[PDB]
Length: 55
Length: 54
Image (tube, rainbow over all chains, first blue to last red; front, side, top):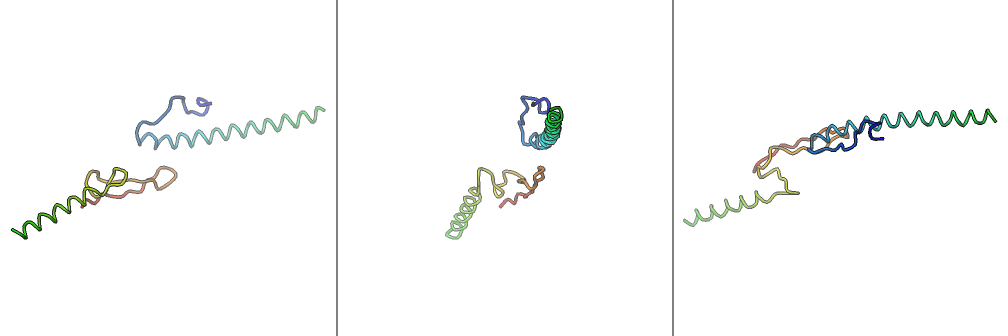
């Protein structure tokens, strides 16, 4: 969610200098979101493998 | 007097030409601002163009 990736809902830029830092903030948000989704993918693969073994 | 009137006419022409060189409301020839910075890199870096008042 927005709070999970550090975006802090109701977060905008009011000047042309705040967007300069919003660029880096969104870069960090995208990086951490991709890391979390990679972890979720690993967990899903593990679930599938264990289901096959149990059968 | 005729030469003086010609001089005055040309000077007014210069002012008219200089004050109308605006694109999108901003200009680098009127003297309204000191410089214009455009985007140069995906990280926010700028390309600086100094204002040349004419």
